[PDB]
Image (cartoon, rainbow, N blue to C red):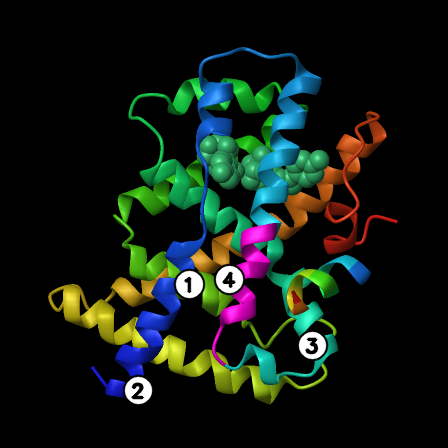
């Protein structure tokens, strides 16, 4: 889940 | 009531209100009967919007940072539909000019969604309007939904429970603060949660059916809802 992980961490 | 509570309430409200719902997109479909595909494209933007502010609100929730990282994801994917429908309800009830409910229902039949699902959507929107839901309630209920410790794939329920309970405690003080004569308000709120829960199924069906009829989504919309 690379994309939500990016939007959670910044 | 409690200082710890007034701080929590306020942190939650600041964050919820920071989330911008530009209404150009909405005034687009209002004033123009587009083509099914072009409506759908507009929906795709609105859906993308929802996920984005979802994640921006969730990031900030006090303590969300301190949860194991795979629980973080699991809460997000589990709450997205419920939270997305709540925010949709707020927009229906606050950010649209009066007397356009029917017109908007036209626009949504037309976007390749079945009546079977439209009827429940707008009823929910209206039931919320009948409760004259406050900005506090939208933001609390949204946070309560996201921090549901009952979701699938949650390794550590209790940690999530810890963060959701104080939210629940606050919401019910405010129900009693602003409606001391209606002790049952809080319970009506929770009944709206149970009704929210029915959208998970409707949503999966809305997607499976869009997909069979050749609609394409976005990566991102595919991640959050595991379309593979
Ligand atoms: C009522 C709505 C139209 C509004 C609130 C929920 C919706 C069903 C839609 O969301 C999508 O799921 C969606 C998913 C993928 C896509 O390409 C477009 C929309 C945005
Ligand atoms: C009735 C509806 C299906 C119609 C208007 C309210 C809705 C819930 C929806 O609005 C958005 O989802 C939306 C999301 C973000 C944004 O900036 C604008 C609209 C389109």
Numbered disc 4: what chain? B
B82 and B57: which is toward the camera: B57
Task: Magenta stretch: give its range.
Answer: B52-62
Which residue is identified by label 1?
B15
B49 vs B40: above or below: below
**In front: label 2 or label 1:** 1
In the picture, the quarter occupied by the N terminus of chain B is bottom left
Mark 2 or mark 1, earlier in chain: 2
- Residue extending farthest front: A10
At numbered mark 1, what does the secondary structure look like: helix, strand or loop? helix
Residue B189 shows up from this direction: yes
Question: Disc number at residue B4?
Answer: 2
**In front: label 4 or label 3:** 4
Mark 1 or mark 4, earlier in chain: 1
Instruction: Report how far apart the C-alphas of labels 2 and 3 lie in the structure.
Output: 25 Å
**In front: label 3 or label 1:** 1
Disc 1: residue Cβ within 8 A of ligand 2's nearest atom: no
Confirm or deny contact between disc 2 and disc 3 (CB under 8 A).
no
Numbered disc 2: what chain? B
B19 and B175: which is toward the camera: B19
B45 vs B84: above or below: above
B12 vs B210: above or below: below
Mark 4 or mark 3, earlier in chain: 4
Confirm or deny contact between disc 3 and disc 1 (CB under 8 A).
no
x and y, in percent, of residue B147 in the image:
54, 72
- Is residue B19 found left or right of B174 in the rendered image? right
């Amino acid at each position: 889940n690379a994309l939500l992980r990016y939007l959670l961490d910044k | 009531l409690t200082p710890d509570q007034q701080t929590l309430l306020h942190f939650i409200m600041d964050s919820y209100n920071k989330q911008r719902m530009p209404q150009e997109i909405t005034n687009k479909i209002l004033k123009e009967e587009f083509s099914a595909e072009e409506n759908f494209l507009i929906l795709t933007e609105m859906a993308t919007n929802h996920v984005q502010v979802l994640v921006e609100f969730t990031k900030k929730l006090p303590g969300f940072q301190t949860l194991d990282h795979e629980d973080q994801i699991a809460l997000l994917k589990g709450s997205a539909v419920e939270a997305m429908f709540l925010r949709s309800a707020e927009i229906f009830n606050k950010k649209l000019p009066s007397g356009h409910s029917d017109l908007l229902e036209e626009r949504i039949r037309n976007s390749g969604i079945s009546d079977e699902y439209i009827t429940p959507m707008f009823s929910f929107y209206k039931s919320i309007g009948e409760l004259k839901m406050t900005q506090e309630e939208y933001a609390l209920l949204t946070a309560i939904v996201i921090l549901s410790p009952d979701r699938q794939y949650i390794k550590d329920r209790e940690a999530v429970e810890k963060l959701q309970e104080p939210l629940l405690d606050v919401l019910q003080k405010l129900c009693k603060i602003h409606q001391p004569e209606n002790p049952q308000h809080f319970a009506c709120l929770l009944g709206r949660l149970t009704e929210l829960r029915t959208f998970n199924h409707h949503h999966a069906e809305m997607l499976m059916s869009w997909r069979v009829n050749d609609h394409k989504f976005t990566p991102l919309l595919c991640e959050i809802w595991d379309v593979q």
